[PDB]
């Protein structure tokens, strides 16, 4: 491969050209280097949060601008840095490349191609700290995001521009719902209608490189990597890089949002973002706050999350949906960061290990799992046309509200008991198996007209699968009609009821 | 036959890495270090004279 | 030539400016520096020494260098005040948010004033008819008073605020101002378009609500001063115009949170459980700036977010002393299905006495409160042991209290997206008579489900009859 | 308005001395007297700087500062006030002397040892830092060659590293 | 070249400050040298303080350190012997052979501090390592290329579990193994050394398949925090240069973070939560990311963690949870219940437990076992106060089946037979899954619950029930 040799030759010649065009005199001198921190004497006119280059080749961000010497964090190890080293100034605030060539690639916090598939075609370069859209330049959420999870679709709706939190405990299924949504978006990501395209952008802050390798292998197996971008900040990387990565990914998604497209961001394990910020603030001798965390972690999370929004028609009616993930220690949602994030998001998706060990694979605590948007951002077929899909929330609350303390009194209580337990066994789903609205509607519609006559509990799963078969075969007209029009008309309600009762008699 | 070619790409860069070791070991045994200071002198003249 | 200073340190939101000239701007003076987009403004809080002042920035400190020219405005933040501010969206430093041009006005008042004197302290005994059963039966609201919506995250504070807006703010009230303090921008847009579609604000016409917004996206400094801007506009309407205004603050806890946010970097030793040592004094200043004077009346309804649904947290606990009719919302009854979620016991008001609401209303309220007390006292017996080992009176009280507690639920006009049931507004005497009838025992045969999500007792009768209907 | 910022930390004494000199006069006489004082204290180091230890009482400090001012009262102007204030405050008197020298040289000299990619030592006796660096560098490269030893210059090594990294 | 020499200024506990001369500043994490009368005292550099002064960490005790002593710079990070010759030689945090078996004749010497192997990472999560222990094989299979949990408090039996693994895995495996042993009792190390000698894994005049690293609690904090990296360096040399399947073993990773917290306070950093070092996650990730499957080769690492005061929410265990795929908590309550191993089946958890990898039948069996065991925990409160007679018939059936199961999870160990009196036994995966499914189906409900204690397969339960009905009843 001689071509990379002359490529490197011209690289080195422009390297010389760029290097010998500075004649800087404010280039500071390193006073002392700490654990990833370096105070430097110099840079009189340095901007805040501005990137720097060390003479060794390590980057740095200007956090503290106290008089005399400047607090510089390190994007990488303090391995190669010593005292008395000349520190080059970029002249610009920390930036990340943005563009459509990102799709199918894996990059780091800064944005360098780390997957090893060549350089990155970037259509632009946006800031890591950009202002959230104002009160007017936005529109309310109306278009629903189809997760493929029946418990996450018919019960806790999400849409373009909302902020749904996957709150839960360790290894409960927090990443599972996100990856399932990413796989589910493939149905419309393969078409031509751009108003229905949902490109996926995912952050990996703190997760080990093996986990992200398995994850990317997953998306490429199901052929979802072509519309997904992975930014990785493993625990091996320095705290500044982990702290910066989610902001860069937010800018990446905001590129699509401002260009009129629709995108989805998964803020996976935003807690280690907080601990990296803790390390940053403590190593900068910044006075800590509650339980050693920096004070402005609420502002940190607010500025990051509120960038996701649904734009109005004037600017292009783009969207950006935030999907953050927070892990809690022993189910303690009263913990500081869990409280901040539950107060910052537009609803939450609670997952707990107890229901997980009860058999419920999604482990969605419908008691606490709530969405600030209901009818809005929901497909109409899973709405008032189905009737009870307006009010299953009350039904699942009451069925839990009479388990043993509300002991069965009369036949109505027994009927509600059977209905509720059959439904809870029905809502079960398996990972790596996203579903579609056109076959959500029949299953839960059967949950109102004939569900207690299901063929015993251990065999309601193949009951739902056989119902799906009996509706995809010999009944494709119903599935189609409900999938393009998106709602159930009067004759369509009659046909659906007829089919449900026909298979009930079967 | 594709990732073998891809591995062929990756391995080729790897011996180029040890080639630089052969290159850099050639860099340290020259009188150019004496000649290189003149390169800065002419370069730094061109630098500030631009200003 | 005004006083000119140089930027010396930029640590987070803290900006330190040295004024080489001996003359120094006092604290609470607004500062002006040239930023590429607009004009970043500062705020002197401490006089460090050696002609150096410590300032907090109302906007982000991104892009600042040490040595930037700083201009002294010579005064606090001036916010436009007047009838022309109605129907406009205003930032923390006065400039409009909505792209509708400059706010043409002739009065600019500082956002830092003094609370009215004791000789100016007024009094009130009027009852605000809200149409909500619970807050009209157990915690009546006083016109020209303080209303506190205590609750956690996801309990329904903002929904209650929107319902109170839709009910009271329309017609009833000379003017009203809504102040968004560290709150979701999506809900701010929701408020804005509901306001525009309802007609309370008319863009080619007269408006009735003034909107100032400081949300979570803004840095702490703006979140600590937007409430004061809203106070300034509300006080200007109350005093000069002699009008009865409706100050609608949301998430007042965010102001104290923003204060604790910059307390540590200011150089103050933290207080208990990580709050600013000066929270009580500053928040007392802010609250006592909210009062009904002899020049006009102000009716304040502000929601208080309790961190981790704890009522013993210093901020909500210290706010409790500033609120006349506290309406605390409880999570438990919220997941029990009663979405009004007003706690029948803990929510207490000062206006509840026989000398104002009438002897009969006081008796009904006391009896229903003690019945709920008795019910919750027996919860252990019912739950872990069993309900069958109770006396007949204990049981009868249990069913009566359950019927009452699910009768406290009411439809909300702004809850159709969630409930799907049309909202209901039940008048005072209607609620009193219905609950008196339920108390006496005239309506014991009706099943409990007919009391759920309903209006008056006539609606309960209709629901019971219709339940018998489809039950066949 | 002193030309440079010493940012305090025991350096504010030098700035105060310079401001006291600048308010009326004697920018040089006080400084040369202080240089003579430092020469005297380094003349007898075992009695010079060991006596600047903090285990030495206040009236001991008064005695030592009175002992400093001899040999035709070389301490001229407000430097005696500096000795007094150092008696009842922080003791050792070497660092702030260097800070004051740095300040007065910025007032009169403006010399910095730049060279960027070159590790030269080109002190520049001129307040205009525009082209005099060219003459200084030319003189320091034509003769001397004090160190001028980059060992290895950064651009080639860093470029090779980034190229082999891909 | 000239020897870089400086003067010691401050000696603060285990922290030493050294002042150097013109442009003589050493590098971070670079070995220094003090000629102590006892021997060599190296001063690993931690931070730079300026003014030609550096803050260093001592790997040995700082006894007899006078300010102004001569220091010498090694010129690089701590160097340790690496190679097959290290097998059978017990070394230390610095690399000197502490087995007094002569000097080490290593051919290569590698630096202690390396970097993670980028994205040259394979992911072969399909190799279920047959352990033999019934509980782990079912609910949390151990991967051959993964990192193994072993959590638990004081005296919960984590070291015994490690000895069982070294007995069942190391013997029948092709590939070198390394035991680092961070901060454990020297008695345990001596027993482990002896046992590998008699077993034949290491022969003083033979092959030897284990490289023995050892840092106990007698070492100062710096050595206890560096010895893990020293052992990891040996593991990395064997995975790369030799291209073998390495089997890294430690005794306690919590001691590493504990020593980091020890040195952090005197290093001059603001304390983190519950008095830990601010650089907890970063340093622990640096330590545990170098240990990885590493495309040219593969590694299995049986980690071991101590929970402080039986707190699973402690920052160090909570942080190390995320860097492990197969975990084992070893809850104490199971220990006072007498079920040894005391692993909690409701918190063991592993990634490999998926129907595609372990099999549909195994997944269903494990799920039903989890349900049966979780119903018991759900009903515990009712059972504890009221009693089992207040439950329903289905609840009674489930609770008695759960009791039988949780008693059947116990298994004798070939290492702890002295503490049980029953010879150790091993059960294959196919046997234990079949036995558990048979018990779940209800085939064995007339059997007394006591018959499931200290047994292997279901046939052992049948035999024990036969004896119990024969003479006991
Ligand atoms: N629907 C499902 N069906 C089967 N297994 C599931 C399902 N959802 C989750 N799991 C399993 O639960 C475990 C945890 O799920 P997941 O990978 O989403 O982790 P997580 O909750 O995000 O946790 P972590 O924070 O540790 O990454 C895995 O073993 C996964 O296989
Ligand atoms: N399988 C077993 N059978 C019998 N006894 C066992 C078993 N496993 C552990 N024990 C007992 O548990 C106790 C503690 O054993 P061990 O030394 O392994 O504890 P540990 O948790 O590793 O300790 P530490 O916290 O001190 O490192 C001993 O009394 C030992 O006999
Ligand atoms: N009266 C009500 N009817 C229906 N839903 C309600 C009602 N009150 C609260 N909710 C539910 O509670 C959720 C949170 O309400 P919100 O006021 O945003 O929370 P907070 O009280 O924390 O501000 C909403 O998404 C809504 O669905
Ligand atoms: Mg996960
Ligand atoms: Mg709210
Ligand atoms: Mg042990």
Image (cartoon, coloured by chain):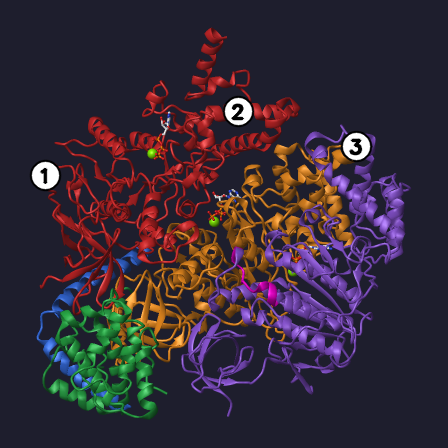
Chain colours: A orange, B blue, C purple, D green, E red
Q: Which residue is mark 3?
A: A410
Q: Is residue A24 visible?
A: no
In depth, the one of A500 and C135 nearer the eye is C135
Report x, y in % for residue C274.
52, 58
Q: Which chain does tag 3 point to?
A: A
Tell us which disc is closer to us: 1 or 2. 1
Q: Quadrant of the N terminus of chain A?
A: bottom left
Does the magenta stretch mainly form a helix, a strand or a loop? Answer: helix
Tell which subunit mark 1 falls on.
Answer: E
Residue lying farthest to the right in this orientation: C442
Q: Find disc 2 in the rendering and name its residue.
A: E403
Left or right: E358 in relation to C472 = left
Q: Residue E202, position in %: x, y?
A: 19, 32
Q: Nearer the viewer, residue D134 or C223?
A: C223
Rendered residue at 61%/41% (across/down): A465
- Disc 1 designates what residue? E102
Magenta residues span C273-282
Determine the chain carrying the residue at label 2.
E
Q: Which quarter of the rendered image does ligand 3 occupy?
A: bottom right
| Labels 2 and 3 positioned on one and the same chain | no
């Amino acid at each position: 491969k001689a071509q990379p040799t002359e490529v490197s030759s011209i690289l080195e010649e422009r390297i010389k050209g760029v290097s010998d065009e500075a004649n800087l005199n404010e280039t500071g001198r390193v006073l002392a280097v700490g654990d990833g921190i370096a105070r430097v004497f110099g840079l009189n006119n340095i901007q805040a949060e501005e990137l720097v280059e060390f003479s060794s080749g390590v980057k740095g961000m200007a956090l503290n601008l106290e008089p005399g010497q400047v607090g510089i964090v390190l994007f990488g190890s303090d391995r190669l840095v010593k005292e008395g080293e000349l520190v080059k100034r970029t002249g610009n605030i920390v930036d990340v490349p943005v563009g459509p060539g990102l799709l199918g690639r894996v990059v780091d916090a800064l944005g360098n191609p780390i997957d090893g598939k060549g350089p990155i075609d970037a259509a632009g370069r946006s800031r890591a700290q950009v202002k959230a859209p104002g009160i007017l330049p936005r529109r309310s959420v109306h278009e629903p995001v189809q997760t493929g999870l029946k418990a996450v679709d018919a019960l806790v709706p999400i849409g373009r521009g909302q902020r749904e939190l996957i709150i839960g405990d360790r290894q409960t299924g927090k990443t599972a719902v996100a990856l399932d949504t990413i796989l589910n978006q493939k149905r419309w990501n393969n078409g031509s209608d751009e108003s229905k395209k949902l490109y996926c952008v995912y952050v990996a802050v703190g997760q080990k490189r093996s986990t992200v390798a398995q994850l990317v292998q997953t998306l490429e197996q199901h052929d979802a990597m072509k519309y997904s971008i992975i930014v990785a900040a493993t625990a091996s990387e320095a705290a500044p890089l982990q702290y910066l990565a989610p902001f860069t990914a937010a800018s990446i998604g905001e590129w699509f949002r401002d260009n009129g497209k629709h995108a989805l961001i998964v803020y996976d394990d935003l807690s280690k973002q907080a601990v990296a910020y803790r390390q940053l603030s403590l190593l900068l001798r910044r006075p800590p706050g509650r339980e050693a965390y920096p004070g402005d972690v609420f502002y940190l999370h607010s500025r990051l999350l509120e960038r996701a929004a649904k734009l109005s028609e004037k600017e292009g009616s783009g969207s950006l949906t935030a999907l953050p993930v927070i892990e809690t220690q022993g189910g303690d949602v009263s913990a500081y960061i869990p409280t901040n994030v539950i107060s910052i998001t537009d609803g939450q998706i609670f997952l707990e290990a107890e229901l997980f060990y009860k058999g419920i694979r999604p482990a969605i605590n419908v008691g606490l799992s709530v969405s600030r948007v209901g009818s809005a951002a929901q497909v109409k077929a899973l709405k008032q046309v189905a009737g009870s899909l307006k009010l299953f929330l009350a039904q699942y609350r009451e069925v839990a509200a009479f388990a043993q303390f509300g002991s069965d009194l009369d036949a109505s209580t027994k009927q509600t008991l059977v209905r509720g337990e059959r439904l809870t066994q029905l809502l079960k789903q398996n990972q790596y198996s996203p579903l579609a609205t056109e076959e959500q509607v029949p299953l839960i519609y059967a949950g109102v007209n004939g569900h207690l006559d299901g063929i015993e509990l251990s065999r309601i799963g193949e009951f739902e699968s056989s119902f799906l078969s009996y509706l995809k075969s010999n009944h494709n007209e119903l599935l189609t009609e409900i999938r393009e029009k998106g709602e159930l008309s009067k004759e369509l309600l009659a046909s659906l009821k007829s089919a449900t009762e026909s298979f009930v008699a079967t | 036959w594709v990732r073998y070619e891809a591995s062929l790409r990756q391995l080729e860069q790897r011996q180029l890495a040890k080639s630089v070791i052969s290159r850099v070991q050639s860099e340290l045994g020259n009188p150019k270090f004496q000649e290189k200071v003149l390169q800065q002198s002419i370069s730094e003249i061109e630098q500030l004279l631009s200003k | 030539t005004p006083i000119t200073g140089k930027v010396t340190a930029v640590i987070g939101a803290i900006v330190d400016v040295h004024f080489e000239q001996s003359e120094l701007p006092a604290i609470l003076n607004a500062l002006e520096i040239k930023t590429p987009q607009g004009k970043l403004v500062l705020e002197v809080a401490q006089h460090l020494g050696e002609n150096t002042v410590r300032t907090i920035a109302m906007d982000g400190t991104e892009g600042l260098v040490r040595g930037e020219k700083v201009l002294d405005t010579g005064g606090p933040i001036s916010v436009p005040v007047g009838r022309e501010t109605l129907g406009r969206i205003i930032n923390v430093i006065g400039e409009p948010i909505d792209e509708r041009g400059p706010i043409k006005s002739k009065l600019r008042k500082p956002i830092h004033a003094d609370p009215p004197s004791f000789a100016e302290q007024s009094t009130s005994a009027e009852i605000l008819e809200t149409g909500i059963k619970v807050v009209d039966l157990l915690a009546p609201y006083a016109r020209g008073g303080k209303i506190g919506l205590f609750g956690g995250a996801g309990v329904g504070k903002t929904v209650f605020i929107q319902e109170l807006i839709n009910n009271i703010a329309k017609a009833h009230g000379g003017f009203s101002v809504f102040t968004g303090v560290g709150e979701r921008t999506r809900e701010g847009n929701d408020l804005y378009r509901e306001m525009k579609e309802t007609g309370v604000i008319n863009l080619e016409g007269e408006s009735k609500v003034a909107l100032v917004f400081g949300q979570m996206n803004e840095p702490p400094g703006a979140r600590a001063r937007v409430a004061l801007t809203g106070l300034t506009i509300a006080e200007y309407f109350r005093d000069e115009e002699g009008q009865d205004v409706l100050l609608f603050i949301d998430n007042i806890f965010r102001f104290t949170q923003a204060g604790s946010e910059v307390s540590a970097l200011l150089g103050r030793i933290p207080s208990a459980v990580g709050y600013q040592p000066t929270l009580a004094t500053d928040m007392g200043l802010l609250q006592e700036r909210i009062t009904t004077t002899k020049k006009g009346s102000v009716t304040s309804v502000q929601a208080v977010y309790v961190p981790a649904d704890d009522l013993t947290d210093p901020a909500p606990a210290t706010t409790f002393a500033h609120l006349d009719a506290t309406t605390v919302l409880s999570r438990g009854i919220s997941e029990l299905g009663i979405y009004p979620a007003v706690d029948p016991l803990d929510s207490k008001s000062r206006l509840l006495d026989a000398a104002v609401v009438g002897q009969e209303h006081y008796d009904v309220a006391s009896k229903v409160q003690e019945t709920l007390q008795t019910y919750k006292s027996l919860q252990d017996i019912i739950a872990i042991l069993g309900m069958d080992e109770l006396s007949e009176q204990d049981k009868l009280t249990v069913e009566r209290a359950r019927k009452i507690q699910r009768f406290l639920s009411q439809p909300f006009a702004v809850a159709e997206v969630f409930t799907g049931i049309p909202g209901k507004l039940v008048r005072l005497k209607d609620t009193v008579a219905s609950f008196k009838a339920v108390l006496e025992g005239k309506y014991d045969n009706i099943p409990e489900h007919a009391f759920y999500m309903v209006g008056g007792i006539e609606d309960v009768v209709a629901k019971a009859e219709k339940l018998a209907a489809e039950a066949n | 308005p002193p030309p440079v910022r010493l940012f305090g930390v025991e350096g504010t004494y030098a700035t105060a001395l310079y401001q006291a000199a600048a308010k009326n006069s004697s920018i040089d006489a006080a400084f040369q007297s202080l240089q003579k004082v430092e020469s005297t204290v380094k003349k007898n180091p075992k009695l010079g700087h060991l006596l600047l230890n903090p285990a030495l009482s206040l009236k001991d400090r008064n005695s030592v500062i009175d002992a400093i001012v001899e040999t035709h009262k070389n301490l001229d102007g407000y430097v005696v006030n500096l000795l007094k204030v150092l008696s009842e405050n922080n003791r050792l008197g070497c660092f702030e002397k260097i800070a004051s020298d740095f300040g007065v040289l910025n007032d009169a000299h403006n010399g910095l040892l730049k060279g960027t990619v070159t590790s030269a030592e080109p002190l520049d006796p001129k307040s205009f830092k525009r082209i005099e660096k060219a003459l200084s560098a030319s003189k320091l490269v034509g003769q001397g060659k004090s160190l001028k030893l980059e060992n290895v210059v950064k651009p080639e090594i860093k470029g090779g590293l980034i190229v082999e990294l891909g």
